[PDB]
Length: 14
Length: 125
Image (cartoon, rainbow over all chains, first blue to last red; front, side):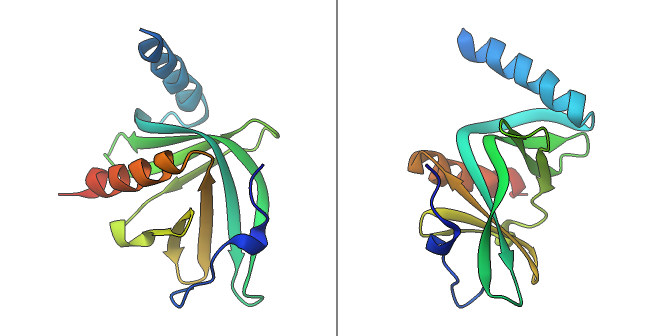
């Protein structure tokens, strides 16, 4: 149901 | 009205766990919690998944509770400053401190955008 952790962004601020 | 009963019942459930909670501001049904590992530069999916409640405590501090339906361990965090919450892609990224980042995924994208606005407006002075 909920996406895999790997789909979450690591943007410039992170 | 169904929502009047739901909110009254939910508030007692929240107050049982956290007596300092004064009111429910808004709710979102299927929210999943992720945690960012700083040194590893990777996201981790936590064991917390359930109903999200945006709340106000007795001192009007804004925060949120996730009532975990899977395991008894719930999550209660404060949103200390509006700039600490960012809508990034499909997630609400809550960074309370440089090294301490959590990510929220809401099943309904309309919940994510509404909750973001309500967070900002709840912190507006």
